[PDB]
């Protein structure tokens, strides 16, 4: 309903992974990146804004999240940007669980794929489309619904 996404960079072995979670639906988006830079982060945001509706972006004070590059990019994309985790108690809950669940799926799929990127895709499909909550609604269905009402 608010389309607020929180992003963070994480590590899975040597691979760095940018991760964004939509707070309302719990929908997860992630992408493997070459290195933790503002340039890569900007590419990730452009991809996110390309595929989904992003009205507000939150993250920690990390350098790659506070560069003028990122600040101006969000202004250009008309995205409200904030810093300093957390945002609100309930959101932090959703985000923490998602990172954990993502890491669990990653541990499962890595042995089934040649690449980490293919393992990440399957891990995201699993989190977003292969589990239900209340009403049997997948995080994907919930997000889609919030999109539809808007």
Image (tube, rainbow, N blue to C red):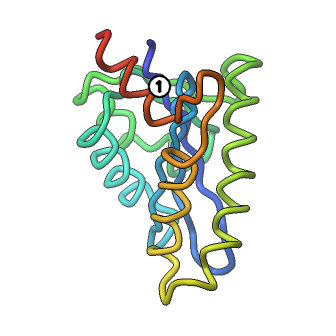
Residue nearest the observer in this picture, 141 or 100:
141
> In which image quadrant can residue 81 be found?
top left
Give the quarter of the figure containing the N terminus.
top left
Query: Residue 15 location in percent, x, y?
Result: 58, 76
Please name the residue shown 31% across and 54% down the image: 43
Please name the residue shown 67% across and 37% down the image: 95
- Determine whether, in the image, residue 102 is placed left or right of residue 72: right
Neighbour tally class for label 1: few under 14, some 14-19, many 20 plus, Cα within 10 Å: some
The image shows residue 111, relative to residue 91, as above or below, that is: below
Query: Residue 122 location in percent, x, y?
Result: 49, 65
- Determine whether, in the image, residue 127 is placed left or right of residue 100: left
Query: Residue 74 location in percent, x, y?
Result: 33, 31
Query: Residue 126 location in percent, x, y?
Result: 55, 55
Give the quarter of the figure containing the C terminus.
top left
The image shows residue 69, relative to residue 81, as above or below, that is: below
Please name the residue shown 74% across and 40% down the image: 96
> In which image quadrant can residue 109 be found?
bottom right
Count the marks: 1
Residue nearest the observer in this picture, 136 or 50:
136
Residue nearest the observer in this picture, 120 or 126:
126
Q: According to the image, label 1 marks what residue? A: 142
The image shows residue 79, relative to residue 38, as above or below, that is: above
Residue extending farthest to the bottom is: 114
Secondary structure beneath dot 1 equals helix
Residue extending farthest to the front is: 136
């Amino acid at each position: 309903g608010s389309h607020l996404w929180q992003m963070d960079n994480t590590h899975w072995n040597k691979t760095i992974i940018w991760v964004a979670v939509e707070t309302n639906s719990g929908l997860v988006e992630a992408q493997v990146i070459p290195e933790e830079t503002a340039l890569q982060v900007a590419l990730c945001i452009l991809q996110l804004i390309q595929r989904y509706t992003v009205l507000h972006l939150h993250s920690d004070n990390g350098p790659c999240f506070t560069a003028h590059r990122i600040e101006n990019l969000c202004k250009y994309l008309g995205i409200t940007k904030t810093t300093g985790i957390p945002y609100n108690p309930q959101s932090q809950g959703v985000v923490e669980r998602a990172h954990r669940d993502l890491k669990d799926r990653l541990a499962a799929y890595q042995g089934d794929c040649e690449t980490v990127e293919a393992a990440l895709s399957l891990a995201l499909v699993s989190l977003n489309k292969k589990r239900g909550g209340i009403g049997g609604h997948t995080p994907y269905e919930i997000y889609l619904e919030s999109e539809h009402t808007k």
